[PDB]
Image (cartoon, rainbow over all chains, first blue to last red; front, side):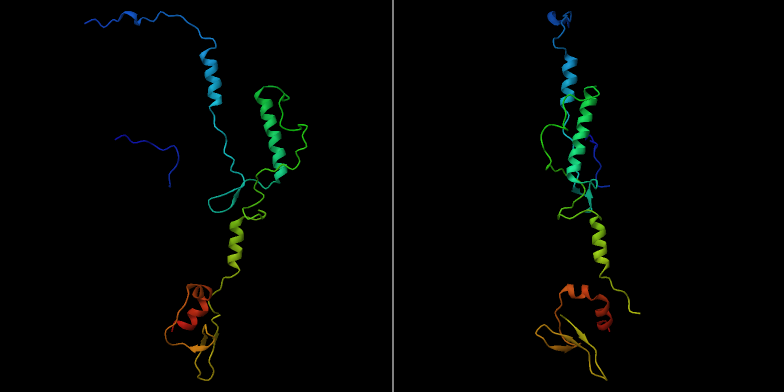
Length: 140
Length: 49
């Protein structure tokens, strides 16, 4: 039985028939290739946003940046990508500097953990110190 | 609240019971594991013999 690999790492009589000739000459409108490439670009799924979520040992994934600053930084990045995609220097469709006073907006980041505290120091480090405070040794 | 008091001049050491009494190192005792986890070294030194 055929073995299927894993893309993701584990835990480690005359034959001739009358009408079959191929002398038809037709061009499509719209063409097949153009719509095929556009559909290929539309097939792509959305990106995974894991910022602000735990690691496999408890530490938070992301960067130590404020949330509103994070939202504005992401808006700038998306606008630059739009300008790149339409090949212009300045984007016609923009996500920043829109005329809406959207100053309370928040985005995920690595600056907070799940209990609401700050990640000035990783969670595993805090566990280690809180445990080290209670150790005892062999009598002198 | 299991506290241990040393003996003096031949008097035997005693340990604090739940009802509030102090009893010597003999008999049948009931411990949760948290007690030995909290006082590993002290309990080892006092009891093992």
